[PDB]
Length: 86
Length: 86
Ligand SMILES: [Zn+2]
Ligand SMILES: [Zn+2]
Ligand SMILES: [Zn+2]
Ligand SMILES: [Zn+2]
Ligand SMILES: [Zn+2]
Ligand SMILES: [Zn+2]
Image 1 (cartoon, each protein chain N blue to C red):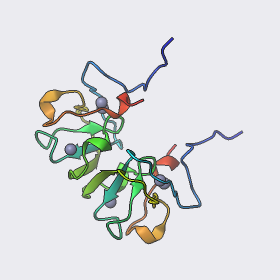
Image 2 (image 1 turned 60 degrees about the vertical axis):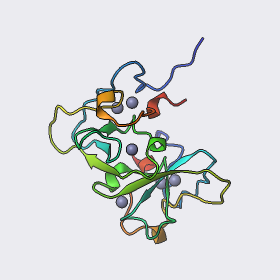
Image 3 (image 1 turned 30 degrees about the vertical axis):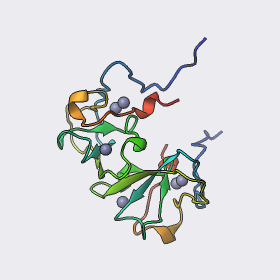
Image 4 (image 1 turned 180 degrees about the horizontal axis):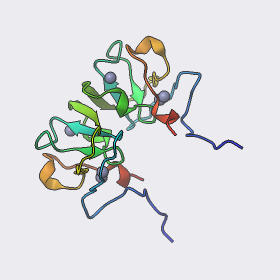
């Protein structure tokens, strides 16, 4: 047996979650390679960002925008996905 | 019948969660009345802080420090506890 983890765990791939209208998300000035790099609520790990300038958002329009957790091109440091924590 | 909510829901009182060593937490420059006002991970709601300067922390020492969610003396605006969201 092996217990199941979080349904948002995505070890081995990019998260790719598509945001819905009204859904919040996170940005980090220091970690994001640019101001389009974002993390969904299931992925953002506060432990990765102590003393960083974090800025939340809410998706307010139909977008093809997606969570960049697990996309190393989007981040300046390793992230530790919150959904991987047990 | 009425379904149970989140075990961290604390409608009607202050949260009061005591942080453990290694536990992350949140601060908001604009919302906190001072730099001692904090929110635990179960309470911090990103929807309350769009375009605010949010700063995470990790508790690194034995403290009597506690989450201030639901303590109106600690905040400059109404918060909407994440644990109340269904
Ligand atoms: Zn994600
Ligand atoms: Zn992730
Ligand atoms: Zn960061
Ligand atoms: Zn709390
Ligand atoms: Zn709360
Ligand atoms: Zn705020």
